[PDB]
Image (cartoon, rainbow, N blue to C red):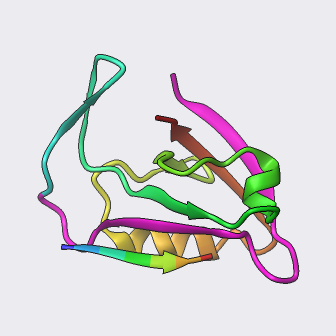
Amino acid sequence: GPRVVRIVKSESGYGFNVRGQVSEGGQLRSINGELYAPLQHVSAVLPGGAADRAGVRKGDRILEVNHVNVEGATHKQVVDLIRAGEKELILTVLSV
Amino acid sequence: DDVQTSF
């Protein structure tokens, strides 16, 4: 099931990478029996960073950023939403 | 394609 993680930004950042489609049109994928449009995913977590300590895990598939749905979004759309957090980030994710 | 960004 989707879970919600709060990450407070440190002076060095959030400590995670996001990878996903540049443009819309990617393949659909079934997760936990539910069909989803393409989801950007957490591709790396800095050990001991803010995201790591908050419980973000590698492979986490991002459904929402600050309660804005990003299912099927472009990479730039997700990047821009994360940067608009400005010292706090709420991720709704589907972990592997 | 797939692209990556660091936060």
Residue A6, percent from left and from top: 76, 48
Residue B1, percent from left and from top: 18, 73
Q: How many marks?
A: 0
The boundaries of the magenta stretch are: A1-25
Q: Is residue B5 left or right of residue A22?
A: right
Q: In this view, does A45 lie above or below A71?
A: below
Q: Which residue lies furthest to the right in this view?
A: A11
For residue A48, what is the image quadrant?
Answer: bottom right
Q: Please check the rendered image and state whether residue A13 is part of the magenta-colored stretch, yes or no.
A: yes
Q: Is residue A59 above or below residue A80?
A: above
Picture residue at 81% right of the left edge, 69% below the top: A9
Q: Please check the rendered image and state whether residue A62 is part of the magenta-colored stretch, yes or no.
A: no
Q: Nearer the viewer, residue A66 or A7?
A: A7
Q: Nearer the viewer, residue B3 or A81?
A: B3
Residue A82, percent from left and from top: 59, 68
Q: Is residue A68 left or right of residue B7?
A: left
Q: Residue furthest top?
A: A33
Picture residue at 35% right of the left edge, 48% below the top: A71
Picture residue at 51% right of the left edge, 48% below the top: A64
Picture residue at 48% right of the left edge, 66% below the top: A18
Q: In this view, does A89 lie to the left or right of A77?
A: right
Q: In this view, does A75 lie above or below A69?
A: below
